[PDB]
Length: 101
Image 1 (spheres, rainbow, N blue to C red):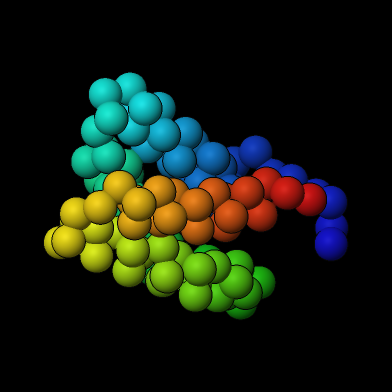
Image 2: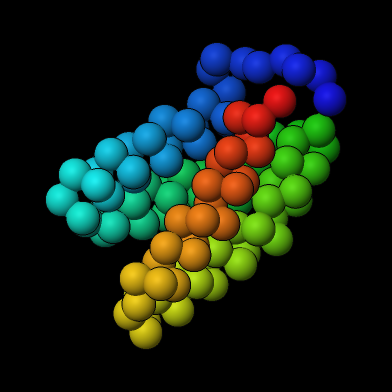
């Protein structure tokens, strides 16, 4: 509860990240881009940490992303928009939180 927001930060990658994924996603119903957007973005967050202060952030969603991530892998393997939508839902929740303040 800081009500503070930074322009050039992680939240910046989420906004711009999802922004592109979504933009491309809706563009030509190509979720491929989205996956390639998070793949790195997410990866970057994994291999590219920040600090104990950010640890809570990655953890806060750590489980969230994990769930949505599973719905993704399940979707990519299985193949179901429903699952895809759910994954997009989970993300929005996390992506929405990072923004919500």
